[PDB]
Structures are given as C-alpha cells and as structure tokens.
Amino acid sequence: SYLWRDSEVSRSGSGDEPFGWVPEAHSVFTERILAEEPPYPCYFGTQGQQRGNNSFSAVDTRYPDTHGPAALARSLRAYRQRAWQGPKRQTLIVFVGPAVPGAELADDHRRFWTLLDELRAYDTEPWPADVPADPSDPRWQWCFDGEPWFIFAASPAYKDRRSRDLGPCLTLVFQVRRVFEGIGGSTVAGKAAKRRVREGLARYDRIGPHPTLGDGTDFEWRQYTLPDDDSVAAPDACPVR
Ligand code: HEM
Ligand SMILES: NC(=[NH2+])NCCC[C@H](N)C(=O)O
Image (cartoon, rainbow, N blue to C red):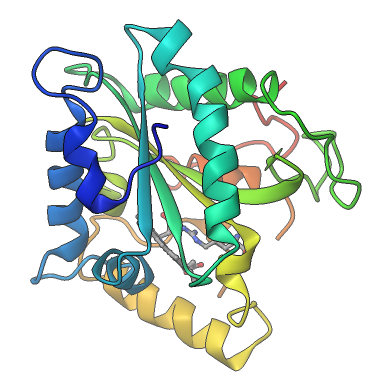
C-alpha cells in the first residue's frame, strides 16, 4: 500500500508523520530528472517520468516495523507485477528518509546494502535458477520475487558524479530486466543509447563515466554503488550476504 504513482505521492504523509518528508523528496527528484539545461543525462529516466512510467515508495528509518523493509518487500512485489504490464520502461524510485545531514557516501552505500539484505528475508519466492546465488560469482545479480533486477543507489553525497545525486535522501532505483529489452550491449540501439547517455554525463558530471559501466558485464554489483571517483572495487568484494 506504499506503492505510489506521481499523483498518489502527496498522500504518503503530511508534516512530521511517517513519510511526511516524502512529498518534498519526490519534488526534488522530479525537478532533477526534468531539468531543462543541462538536461538530466539519462533521457530514459526523463522520458519515463514524463510518460507516467515511474512509481515510488519509501522507507522511514524511524519506524522500521511498519514503514521499513517488510513493507518495502510488499511494495516491491506489487511493483514487479506493475512492471510487467504496459510500458516496458518503468522504474521504481524508493526514498529512504528522513534525510541525514552530512552523511558520507560510504555511509549511504552501507545503508543501501543493509536494506537489500533485510529485503532478502521478506522474499516469498526462491532465488532464480538462472542466476548464481553466490555474490562473488561474475554472473551474480540481485534477485527478488523470482527474478533479477537492476538496482542502484543515489545519494546527495555524490558530489562529482552529480547524475547520482537525486536529492537529500539515499534513494534506491529498481528496475526489472525488461527495461533493457531492445537496447542490449551488442545491439545498434544499445550502443546508441550508451553514446547518448554518456554525452549527457559529459555535460552534467564533474567526472566521466565510471570504468565499471564498461566500454559501451561480469560483477554487475559494482554498478549498483559507483564511487564518486575512479576507484574500482575488488570484484569478489560485494557486501551482500
Ligand atoms: C528514474 C529513472 C532513471 C534514473 C534515475 C536513471 C539514471 C541513470 C544514471 C545516473 C545513469 C548513468 C550511469 C549510472 O550512474 O549508473 C544512467 C545510464 C543509463 N540508463 Fe538510466 N535512469 C533511469 C531510467 C532508465 C530506464 C527506464 C532505462 C531503460 C532503458 C535506462 C537505461 C540507461 C542506460 C542504457 C544507461 C547507460 C549505461 C551506460 O552508458 O553504460 N535508464 N541512468
Ligand atoms: N543506470 C544504469 N547504469 N543503467 C544501465 C544498466 C544496464 C545493465 N547493466 C544491463 O546489463 O542491462
């Protein structure tokens, strides 16, 4: 019941109630993604926003038993069903709040991995057979509710990689793999997509595309939590589990 379309987010909370900080986080996020000049680097995200294809949820760290990982697992199951109907290019954006002034990027990434770990406990489906369960396997991807996802962390502590600063809260961006159908890495369209996004990053960010994004697949976990510099994590060092 915490899965929201744009028009529903304002009813999340009002004032100091649980989620009372969500409507403002939603507005900061949409302002970032819809900004005109320079445009947000990912036109897919911008187009998804414009087309009503982004859904939202939240975690309120003050109330983990009612507004935390158990509820987010329910929201994610509902989102997964939604993501397989209508437009292929949908995204779920989950704000984790209230915001913590001065948090370091490493702290927000720690919080990200901890939240994924807490979700695994609430998964009602077995881990997919086509995906290795061992997070040190080159082919590991995070899975939930019977399928792999692409998931990444955004944080206000991304100072140079501004594309990943979506507002004052740690923000989790979830997609089922369906979003990439038609823009695989070998495809003409997929190469054009990476060109276009990376041109956008070269007009928006203070640091270029991270090496773990590739030239334009092993150890995808490193993409979930890009650093703010050119450091490259050890491949077998995924924090999950
Ligand atoms: C609110 C939704 C979205 C946000 C906030 C978002 C954000 C980003 C960001 C920050 C990047 C730069 C690389 C990175 O930091 O990981 C990126 C790249 C990209 N996004 Fe999105 N995105 C969104 C939706 C989508 C959707 C729906 C697709 C579906 C096709 C998509 C496809 C891509 C691709 C292909 C890249 C390029 C990867 C590369 O150059 O190697 N995005 N996006
Ligand atoms: N935000 C992003 N980096 N999006 C692109 C994710 C693509 C994903 N690594 C794949 O193999 O399909």
